[PDB]
């Protein structure tokens, strides 16, 4: 709530699984929640879960901070192939400090470049994140 803002470096360890997520995904929707910390100054994985749905990804753990969850959904497009459009929704709900928001919102562009993320999204709450948006998000 009173700290400075810098971009984070991605350690190979978490970067590997960050890449493995898109290369080795399920036929269900999976999510990798990751963290940009200024104190480590590195972008590290908070946790990865599979076979669950959007409601769990937001509910499993209280963030009290701008955390971003990369959800990969098996979504087929008109070109006859089932694709894996994964998006990282950085949610800044109850507890999130202003500078930290901009901290995560800052390096969230870099992670989109790292894993070649399909898209990303931001919502300021935990409760209003659920299945309803998926069919209007895709």
Image: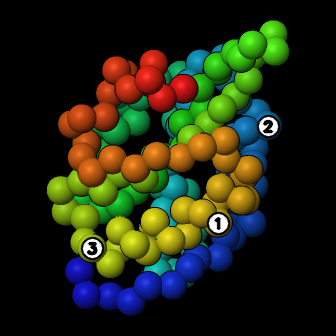
Residue in the picture at 40% in, 36% down: 57
Between circles 2 and 3, the one closer to the viewer is 3
Residue in the picture at 64% in, 19% down: 75
Q: Nearer the viewer, residue 31 or 134?
A: 134
Q: Where is residue 13 in the image (x, y as percent from the top left)?
A: 71, 62
Q: On residue 82, which mark appears?
A: none
Q: Is residue 28 left or right of residue 92?
A: right
What is the spatial separation of the Cα atoms under label 2 and label 3, in whole angstroms? 34 Å
Q: Where is residue 39 in the image (x, y as percent from the top left)?
A: 45, 83
Dot placed on the residue nearer the N-terminal end, 1 or 2: 2
Q: Specify whether residue 80 is in view.
A: yes
Residue in the picture at 59% in, 18% down: 28
What is the spatial separation of the Cα atoms under label 1 and label 2, in whole angstroms? 19 Å
Q: Nearer the viewer, residue 136 or 82?
A: 136
Dot placed on the residue nearer the N-terminal end, 3 or 1: 3
Number of disc labels: 3
Which residue corresponds to mark 2? 23
Dot placed on the residue nearer the N-terminal end, 2 or 3: 2
Say few, some or many: other residues with alpha carbon within 10 Å of mark 3 (under 14 / 14 to 19 / 20 or more): some
Helix, strand or loop at mark 1: helix
Question: Split into 4 quadrants, where in the image is the N terminus?
Answer: bottom left
What is the spatial separation of the Cα atoms under label 3 and label 1, in whole angstroms? 20 Å
Q: Where is residue 123 in the image (x, y as percent from the top left)?
A: 33, 47
Which residue corresponds to mark 1? 110
Q: In this view, does 81 lie to the left or right of 117?
A: right
Q: On residue 98, which mark appears?
A: 3
Q: Is residue 57 left or right of residue 40?
A: left
């Amino acid at each position: 709530m009173t700290s400075s803002l810098t971009i984070c470096s991605i350690p190979d360890g978490v970067k590997e699984d960050l890449k493995k997520f898109r290369f080795s995904k399920s036929t269900t929707m999976n999510a990798l929640i990751l963290k940009i910390d200024r104190e480590s100054h590195e972008l590290q994985s908070e946790q990865l879960l599979n076979d669950c749905s959007i409601e769990e990804f937001k509910e499993e753990l209280p963030s009290q901070q701008p955390r971003f969850i990369l959800l990969s959904w098996c979504k087929k497009h008109s070109d006859e192939r089932i694709s894996y459009p994964m998006l990282l929704i950085y949610y800044c709900p109850n507890g999130s400090s202003p500078e930290l928001q901009m901290l995560y919102a800052g390096s969230r562009n870099f992670i989109v470049n790292e894993c070649h993320v399909s898209k990303n999204t931001e919502i300021r709450d935990i409760d209003e994140i659920d299945d309803e948006l998926l069919e209007s998000k895709f």
